[PDB]
Image: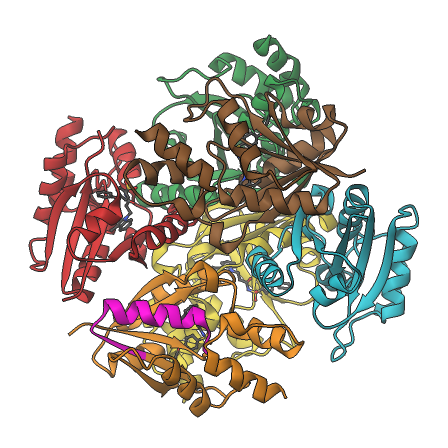
Chain colours: A red, B brown, C green, D orange, E yellow, F cyan
Amino acid sequence: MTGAVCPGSFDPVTLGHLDVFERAAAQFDEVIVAVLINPAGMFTVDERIEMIRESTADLPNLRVESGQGLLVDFVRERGLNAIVKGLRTGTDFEYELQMAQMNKHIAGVDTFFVATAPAYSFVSSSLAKEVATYGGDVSALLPASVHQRLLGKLR
Amino acid sequence: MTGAVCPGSFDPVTLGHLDVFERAAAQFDEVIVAVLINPNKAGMFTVDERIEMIRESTADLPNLRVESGQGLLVDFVRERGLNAIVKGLRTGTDFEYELQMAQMNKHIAGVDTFFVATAPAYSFVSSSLAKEVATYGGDVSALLPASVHQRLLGKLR
Amino acid sequence: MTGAVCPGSFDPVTLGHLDVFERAAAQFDEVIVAVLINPNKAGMFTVDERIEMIRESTADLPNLRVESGQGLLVDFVRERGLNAIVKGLRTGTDFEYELQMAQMNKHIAGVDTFFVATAPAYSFVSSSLAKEVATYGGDVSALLPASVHQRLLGKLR
Amino acid sequence: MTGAVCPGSFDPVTLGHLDVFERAAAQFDEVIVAVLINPAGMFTVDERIEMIRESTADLPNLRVESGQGLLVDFVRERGLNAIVKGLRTGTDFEYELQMAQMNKHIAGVDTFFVATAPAYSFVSSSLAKEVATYGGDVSALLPASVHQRLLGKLR
Amino acid sequence: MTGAVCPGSFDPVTLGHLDVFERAAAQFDEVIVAVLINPNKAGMFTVDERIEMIRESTADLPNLRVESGQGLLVDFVRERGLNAIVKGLRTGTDFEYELQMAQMNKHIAGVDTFFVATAPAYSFVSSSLAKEVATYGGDVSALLPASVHQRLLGKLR
Amino acid sequence: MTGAVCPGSFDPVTLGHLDVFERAAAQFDEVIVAVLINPNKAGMFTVDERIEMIRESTADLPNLRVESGQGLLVDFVRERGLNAIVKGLRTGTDFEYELQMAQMNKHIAGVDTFFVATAPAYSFVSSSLAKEVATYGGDVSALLPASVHQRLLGKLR
Ligand SMILES: Cc1cn(CCC(=O)NS(=O)(=O)c2ccc(Oc3ccccc3)cc2)c2ccccc12
Ligand SMILES: Cc1cn(CCC(=O)NS(=O)(=O)c2ccc(Oc3ccccc3)cc2)c2ccccc12
Ligand SMILES: Cc1cn(CCC(=O)NS(=O)(=O)c2ccc(Oc3ccccc3)cc2)c2ccccc12
Ligand SMILES: Cc1cn(CCC(=O)NS(=O)(=O)c2ccc(Oc3ccccc3)cc2)c2ccccc12
């Protein structure tokens, strides 16, 4: 009965995120994507959840749920104590390590880091939005659904 | 007579800070903890509260004193006849920026900066992260002086 | 026919920037300093002021010109028939973020980014730190071109 | 049927290693500690395996096996495709990332990184040996069994 | 007339190297790939083999030539009337050491070093790691020029 | 009564080292430069040569003395009744390894390690790189004290 939580705002979910979801889903019996409620972003929580659900339909053991407050509480309240977090090029890994040690200290939750695929290693939700805002083509970097939804917000 | 200044907002002081204070006090004749007054820096504790929390925490350090300060750190340092800063390193420290500031501070005022890593036990606490965790009911009592922890629960009530 | 773009907000240009300009001008047939402007946040200097300070300190570089822009850097670059960015590295540079943007810029527009470390003497100055230090009286005169220093003091007073 | 491999020379196994073993054993159904054969070290492969087995006796789902050649082959030949690797203070993380991306590329094996506990974050097999060699006390940093075995090699 | 030197042992040349070669050739009038002769550096391919593998790989780059070299890189560079080095960055690059060498090379000879990150697809290959993986039957054919891969299987037989 | 140890192999001492010595001597009552020797590998200079080169370039520091040692640095430090190490940081420093050793040294012996960034001008010299560059004719005269430079050339010839 293994399980891990993949946390983020996912505003919107990128292929970097999806790659890590897929790896977590492949290595743990159960995966929960934890979507932060914290309203200043582009998509509402429902939209962000929809985009992830749309993009992970072939992952039967993954579910998507919103959450707020301490991540470790989100994880523990679901009977788990593992976080799986992706690494990309602009990741502040020092801060990730700090949070990982804090999360272990206060709640006994482990954090496993996995580098996303090289092809998806330079996209981030923020940079994708920024580039798309100014007409740049990020279609190769987002789930096809997300990409269309993004164009909708901009136009 | 040797001396160094340990700078920060300390909002609140953590055991990470205290560990470095203790090491500074052990290695310099005089240590001044310089507590930032910053009207436009958002914070939880007043300067007087922050100073008092540090004084409680450093009661066993007779050669360390706590003072408020504003503006250029190197002026604070040089005004007190010193020319050394002792700053802690923790997990999540922006060390590249620390280096930049250290080189800037040496250039503009001749002040040296000595960095000390805090003990592993206290390496992942920060003032900001302690506040955030405590705000949502997380137990950071092992990472803060007892008196600080008590005051923190007080501000959150 | 070779060429590169040297981007930044240059608010104000520093000697660290000028070092990088000089190296780009020495290695590419033409160099365009791209003064990138956020239309939704005024900096300390207006665009015309930023450009004037850069021109005055680059007058000895015949193959360098200065233009402002906004939006995607790669559009600025490609619209000038170029395909290269030269970006300086200094102490405190967020290199991981620079790498991320370089890989993104190559992906969306085929533009290459060349990084060069600025000279040690100028390696700890940044526009932001120079402004912050000068704000509180610190002497940054040796880290800025003459075209900048007193104009900076002027803005602050 | 989840599983991961924890690889190393483990010469000798430290509490930093053990902490990560325990986390991997807690989060995966099956864990294999892969002990490299590559003879220039202090302990023989049998001794290194013994020390790990001794230190992990309360981990029923962990086993210890020697291996050589490509790690991904070791992992795949056991029906797995996950590596769990620890991070400590002196870890060359850039090289770890390079190897992780290479291992994913050539064999579809994921690497999950987990930071060892702060208390065990500055011990390494090499530094423990070096310090102990010169009379320094590393007993708080090694399994009690290992520590005694180390003193035996030195004296 | 602009120019840069791309230095390495290239034992063997990888698609990471080639990507950077291509970008250099696109941005400078002349590029020289400088192939290290190093009697005490253990290696798999002879200098002539390494040069030939690079030439095969760069056949479409008319302004790039491949030459062997020994000793101080900056002398190699300056002897050919150039004063720029273009070096790739990959995952596992010791960038702090690269920076040190770049600053040293600028100091002793006035030679600039421009760094370019190789494409993400080729960011995790290195000459050493390719050899090690191939030695144990791992497939690195997607990471090497075809001719290189063929020669590599040949050396391992 | 305050004091610190400045450790290294100093083979040879560089101006980067001397910078750190001067800063330690200015901030601690006494400083001991610890010339740490590996009895199982001769460097370029014998212990007496290393010490002589350091003494000649530190003659203006009355509170600094120079001694050799081997084995655990913390034993060298504690045997002199001290509890502090001052270690320089430069470009190319393996800081993670320094941090690891600092935490280990605190753990086994209660000794504190203070890090200080050496001056930008001396930030890219290292004993090893200076030796390598000088080996192939590169001019490192501005990065080494006079007590070293020609003795270095002597060893190489
Ligand atoms: C799977 C994956 C994650 N990341 C990092 C994304 C990230 O941290 N976004 S974030 O805005 O900062 C963030 C972090 C933690 C949070 O904790 C909670 C979440 C829900 C409820 C309460 C707390 C919330 C938001 C990735 C990067 C690349 C490839 C894959 C991945
Ligand atoms: C573990 C540890 C981390 N730090 C860093 C703390 C820090 O930087 N806080 S800060 O908010 O950003 C900051 C920095 C510099 C300042 O300079 C002045 C101070 C007073 C008057 C004028 C200027 C002010 C605030 C420590 C420092 C000392 C011992 C231990 C540690
Ligand atoms: C669980 C854990 C691992 N490490 C890192 C230890 C390490 O890499 N040792 S190593 O000598 O370099 C090494 C690496 C990979 C290898 O791959 C193979 C192994 C067996 C057969 C074929 C290949 C072999 C040796 C840790 C650090 C701290 C806390 C916990 C951990
Ligand atoms: C992806 C990528 C990585 N690198 C680094 C390759 C590298 O450093 N190899 S190295 O063995 O260590 C090396 C370095 C410098 C040298 O200088 C001389 C060369 C010739 C004659 C005298 C000196 C020699 C060897 C690249 C470089 C160019 C384009 C792309 C990339």
Residue C59, picture quadrant: top right
Residue A142, picture quadrant: top left
Question: Is residue D135 positioned above or below A148 on the image?
Answer: below
Residue D124 included in the magenta stretch of the image: no
Number of labels in the image equals 0
Asked whether, in this view, residue A49 is left or right of residue F136, the answer is: left
Q: Is residue E17 visible?
A: no
The residue under the point 72% across, 67% down is: F75
The residue under the point 50% across, 12% down is: C48
Q: Which residues are magenta?
A: D12-32
Residue D24 included in the magenta stretch of the image: yes
**Within the displayed image, which quadrant is ligand 2 positioned in?**
top right
Residue F135, picture quadrant: bottom right
Locate the C terminus of chain F and report the quarter of the image it occupies.
Answer: bottom right
Q: Nearer the viewer, residue F51 or D95?
A: F51
Asked whether, in this view, residue F105 is left or right of residue F149, the answer is: left
Determine the main secondary structure of the stretch shown in magenta.
helix
Q: Nearer the viewer, residue C100 or D94?
A: D94
Q: Nearer the viewer, residue A8 or F79?
A: F79
Asked whether, in this view, residue D138 is left or right of residue D100, the answer is: right
